[PDB]
Image 1: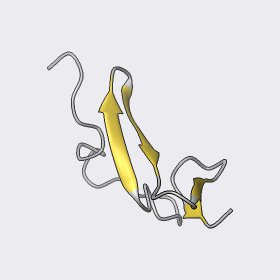
Image 2 (image 1 turned 90 degrees about the vertical axis):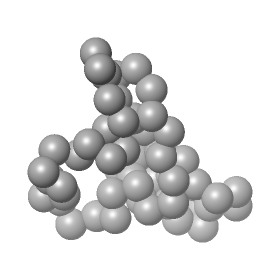
Image 3 (image 1 turned 180 degrees about the vertical axis):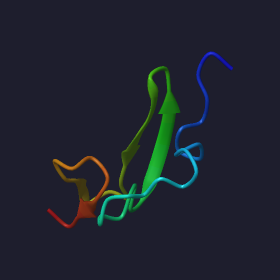
Length: 53
């Protein structure tokens, strides 16, 4: 639509970045999407990888 589920719609799977894009789980919203993690873990500064800190 005006926006889309960028969690899915990452272009033609454009993961041209050696990181686990959205390691745990996404959240779609205006502007596209973001991610989060299973509790205890934390989304790192890269905003895609979750670590246990």
